Image: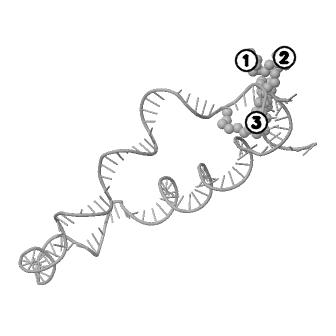
Amino acid sequence: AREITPVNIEEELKSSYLDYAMSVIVGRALPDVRDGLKPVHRRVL
DNA sequence: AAAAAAAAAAAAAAAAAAAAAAAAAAAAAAAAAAAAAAAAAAAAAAAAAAAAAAAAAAAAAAAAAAAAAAAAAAAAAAAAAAAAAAAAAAAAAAAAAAAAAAAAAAAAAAAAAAAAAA
């Protein structure tokens, strides 16, 4: 509950980039093996 | 033959622009009244000129408002600190003349083709 807190460049970069990488890999890039559709195709259909 | 950089595939992030149609305003560029300014004519109040004159500076001298001296007291202006306005100095720049490289027209002449004669 403080206006400013320290954050390391390493921790912030690692958390943000890992979140983005996992989100992309699981949610837009690769298709599921079962139905063979990405989430965009699944939602559109 | 090694290094480096472009480009393309597909789901994601985020932007930009041209016109039509009417009615009003705001810039911005013109003709066109309208008055300063200037050239060139005749024309007419002012200086000149002269004689003649009388109104205000000199001069005597008193006296009455005065400018320096004395004192008390009020407080305007000057110089030192800071804080804004407004103008030359210097440097930079976008079109703009100069130069150099690529596209289109040109015919001279021949390869290949098409066509026909005897």
Q: Is residue B13 above or below residue B80?
A: above
**Camera-side mark, 1 or 2:** 1
Which residue does the numbered mark 3 point to in the structure image?
Answer: A12
The answer as to whether the residues below labels 3 and 1 share one chain is yes
Q: Residue shown at 80%/24% (left/top)?
A: A26
Q: Is residue B20 above or below residue B88?
A: above
Question: What colour-coding does the image apply?
Answer: one colour
- Whole-Å distance between the Cαs marked 3 and 1? 34 Å
Please tell me whether mark 3 sits on a helix, a strand or a loop: helix
Q: Amino acid at mark 2?
A: Arg
Please tell me whether mark 2 sits on a helix, a strand or a loop: loop
- Whole-Å distance between the Cαs marked 1 and 2? 17 Å
Which residue does the numbered mark 1 point to in the structure image?
Answer: A44
Q: Is residue B14 above or below residue B39?
A: above
Decide which of A24, B21 is in the foreground and name it: B21
Q: Is residue A33 above or below residue B81?
A: above
Please tell me whether mark 1 sits on a helix, a strand or a loop: helix
Which is more N-terminal, label 3 or label 2? 3
Decide which of A1, B97 is in the foreground and name it: B97
Disc 1: which chain?
A
Q: Residue shown at 84%/16% (left/top)?
A: A34
**Camera-side mark, 2 or 3:** 2
Contact between labelled residues 2 and 1, with CB atoms less than 8 Å apart: no
Decide which of B31, B110 is in the foreground and name it: B110
Q: Quadrant of residue B2?
A: top right
Which is more N-terminal, label 1 or label 3? 3
Q: Residue shown at 76%/39% (left/top)?
A: A9
**Camera-side mark, 3 or 1:** 1
| Badge 3 density bin: few <14, some 14–19, many ≥20, Cα 10 Å | few
Which residue does the numbered mark 2 point to in the structure image?
Answer: A34
